[PDB]
Image (cartoon, rainbow, N blue to C red):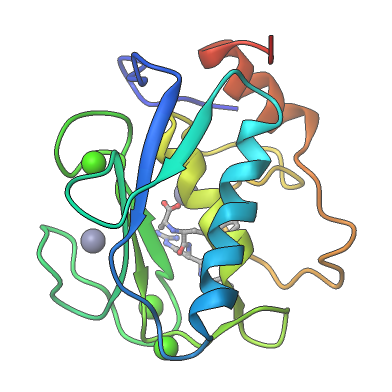
Length: 168
Ligand SMILES: C[C@@H](N[C@@H](CCc1ccccc1)C(=O)N[C@@H](CCCNC(N)=[NH2+])C(=O)Nc1ccccc1)C(=O)O
Ligand SMILES: [Ca+2]
Ligand SMILES: [Ca+2]
Ligand SMILES: [Ca+2]
Ligand SMILES: [Zn+2]
Ligand SMILES: [Zn+2]
């Protein structure tokens, strides 16, 4: 696995997130679930905990957008870049943005929001890209035949634990 240069990481174990807005593709509940599951993935292997906020600034601000969306990294329309997030830190750092120009499905027929959310969150916590192809943190998304066979690789776990340690 690889972490970001300088090894930036949250200096606290309890992070707040806030789904700023939703995609029209899925009902609010399918979106909420996808992100709770997303975070749960990391919560299970570290001493990290998360609480949701509806107002103000959360550590991880989550939102769906297209093309120019208020940052130095515009989305590219359909395909290619699906979403992007920022390594741990203040302000925009830690936030995750999802290209709403994709078709967010809750399965593998389009772009699965659960998986993408899971990968991007890996970035919000300090994990960069892995060279292992079976690792969630691998550079490219790929159509999983099964969402029921998904699990973090020992690599993704090794990495997150090297940063926040194992769960107490
Ligand atoms: C770029 C950004 N977002 C990635 C997430 C990919 C991912 C991996 C594993 C699970 C879920 C999601 C992203 O959007 N990647 C694109 C490709 C970017 C290519 N850029 C480049 N080579 N310079 C991606 O995987 N796209 C894609 C689109 C349709 C189907 C399959 C994959 C990042 O993490 O740095
Ligand atoms: Ca933030
Ligand atoms: Ca795109
Ligand atoms: Ca969309
Ligand atoms: Zn953005
Ligand atoms: Zn990535």
